[PDB]
Image 1 (spheres, chains in turn red, brown):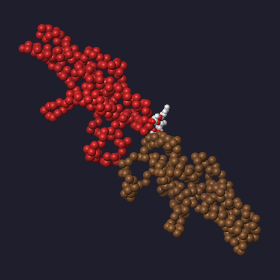
Image 2: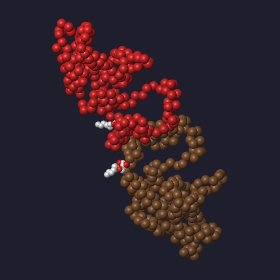
Image 3: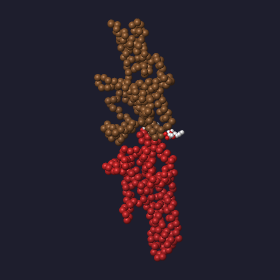
Length: 255
Length: 255
Ligand SMILES: CCCCCCCCO[C@@H]1O[C@H](CO)[C@@H](O)[C@H](O)[C@H]1O
Ligand SMILES: CCCCCCCCO[C@@H]1O[C@H](CO)[C@@H](O)[C@H](O)[C@H]1O
């Protein structure tokens, strides 16, 4: 796990837990009346072992390799006959406990504003199926309205914040443009103090080192300081903005 | 196989071949309209892995042991995930060929009047699914009317012949009973010549030895000489009959 990308590691881990637990949601009367119209054949009177490899020709960009397909096919008969009727209690329970503790340690350091709407939505189910009555679930439910957005069309969902990146770009554009009226000074200061306050300085809570994470020291995020994720792209623009504002007079922009 | 009983070995071997080939008969319109009324639940909408161990309390005489059930459960996941989607070509083909050649070598020596109606019926299907157009199948079909029988009730099926055993018992009873009228001599001779002709003297065709069979030399069967199966029960009565008839005068019973 210390080799794969961070996004894949944080997305597939709840998927791994859900697959291990084999959790299925309750079959409401809507589900039974809607599952028939979707499939072209009867719901329960079809096969599933040979239906696993059927890729559409419209949504196919990177086809699977022969080795990957062979590995998946071998794993299907290696795991399902074994860890479903005679599951290894020790191994499976340790894996589930490690996944749960890793998710709990990750969300606390991320202030429950974890990367990705899909990842947060899946983590909410992952923590709800473990304890429907807790405080982590309630706090996850509380940050849900932080992603909805409205536009000319109906309500949409914002994948992640981008205020810092656009603010830095706008500040750079304003300082590069000639100060004709010179009245942009108050706005420049009122943005510069926010930029200074947006710097992430504290280390992640707990043993962030040796936990499949990288050291963060005076780093910048892409969305906001409440996330605490290092990203070299935004830091490079922030440093340029700070250096360009450094040569500006103190009496006009402030400290 | 040289350890188990002969009847079990000759009965389960066609069962083994049928299970290995996974042969299923054609689904006629009668089958689809009759498979629904039998099962209390829908035909295809039920489970089968956990339905394997459900023994009735009326037809249970020798319950399965824990070790036997564990062995079957382990074999179910050892064989089905392996030898159904990725079958060992060499091992399975050699096993099927050996079963076919063993059945063919056994039926030729048995003159197609093999032991048991169920075993013969299963062997007929086993040889038909291999070659519907042959001579062994036709000769098996020709000996079918050798088992049907009629009585006061409707037509029945006779599992095996018993003419020799009853003939020996009747001959012993007649010779033990005092010859009052002494006119039973012609009948005694007309039965004694048949008894002499009923002795199995030839060895089974081919290499009967070292083929999971026992040596037969001047043995007797239970049904008729056309079978060629050693049985110590009938031989003991036949020897007693021969010895008791030996002391009888030659001029009255013949040679
Ligand atoms: C030291 C070996 C102990 C037995 C291991 C059996 C194979 C692992 O398999 C698991 O083991 C569990 C505990 O026995 C059982 O519930 C089942 O056999 C199975 O779930
Ligand atoms: C020397 C190994 C050759 C490949 C055999 C793999 C194990 C045998 O097993 C069988 O072999 C088939 C033929 O390859 C494959 O379809 C599957 O592995 C299986 O059906």
